[PDB]
Length: 29
Image 1 (cartoon, helix red, strand yellow):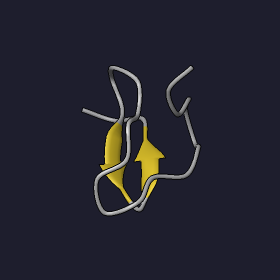
Image 2 (cartoon, helix red, strand yellow):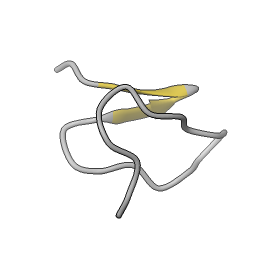
Image 3 (tube, helix red, strand yellow):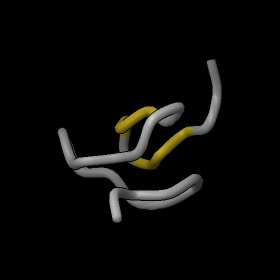
Image 4 (cartoon, one colour):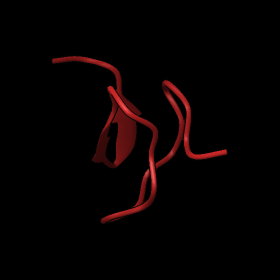
C-alpha cells in the first residue's frame, strides 16, 4: 500500500490520499 500518514516520501513518491509527498507524507490540508 502507498505511503501512510507520517511515512516517507521522495521528491515524488507514491503517497496515499489526504497526504502530501513533500519529503514526508504530511497529513494536512
